[PDB]
Length: 99
Length: 99
Ligand SMILES: COc1ccc(S(=O)(=O)N(CC(C)C)C[C@@H](O)[C@H](Cc2ccccc2)NC(=O)O[C@H]2CCC[C@@]23CCO[C@H](c2ccccc2OC)C3)cc1
Image 1: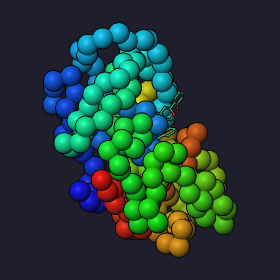
Image 2: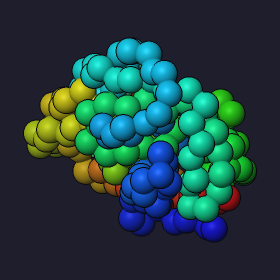
Image 3: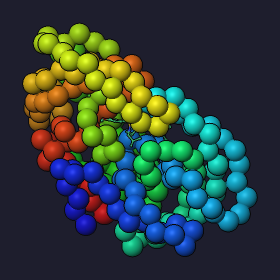
Image 4: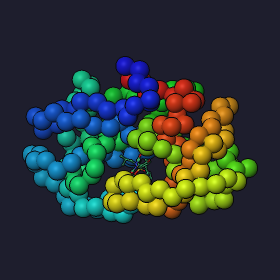
């Protein structure tokens, strides 16, 4: 699709058998999802943003369907105000910024 | 142009007579720029992201040059580590996300 930016670019994603809504976020290197249960081993880690840092759990090799496109990558799980799909997954669905 | 996302989507902008490097950020509602003086009046605002909030100064009707386009709009100035071009200006340069 072609997504204009008059509204937040929210999409439906499928992760760990659950549907979620998430924001396509070209300004985020990594993907950060609100607290949820995922299978497999995770590592504790901290990440930062504009206001400070948060504690997250890092899951590797997670399959995610982003607006019906399949991708695999690392997902960080923690207390984010919005689920954000970062560049590590945007590249894998072939997303580009065009103007 | 068409900008892929294997690296950060950084561009040179001209604002307040100065050249700065900034991120084209679909996840940002507004544009947030590091501390500088701009020639206009400002109002206080607080914005929130991952980790908490920061206090910024809101300037209106600021002209910013982004790759052959001139956008005019609101700019938030505050303690951000990275200059962020948000949707309020991305719409004016006709930017879309495509996949
Ligand atoms: C109303 O207007 C606004 C309101 C809020 C915002 S916003 O900016 O809050 N946002 C909103 C989004 C979180 C919903 C835009 C988002 O695209 C930021 C941009 C940004 C880039 C660089 C530095 C700081 C902000 N990406 C980010 O937060 O990406 C972080 C989180 C995961 C990947 C990330 C990349 C940058 O390095 C981070 C990091 C890691 C370790 C240590 C310190 C760190 O960072 C200080 C990690 C804007 C406008």
